[PDB]
Length: 27
Image 1 (cartoon, rainbow, N blue to C red):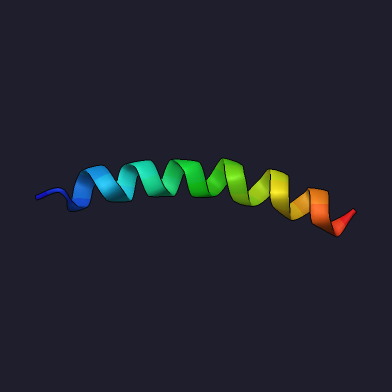
Image 2 (cartoon, one colour; image 1 turned 90 degrees about the horizontal axis):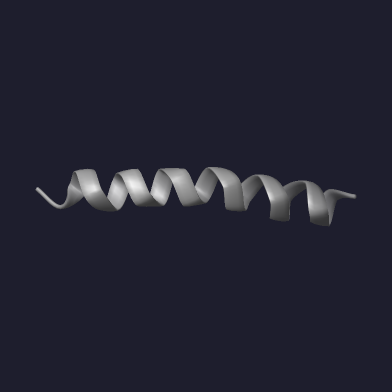
């Protein structure tokens, strides 16, 4: 059930990473 680990790590990193890189490239 490594789906919980990969999903948790991917969701967290994706949130912070998507925001910074998101607003950074947007402005």
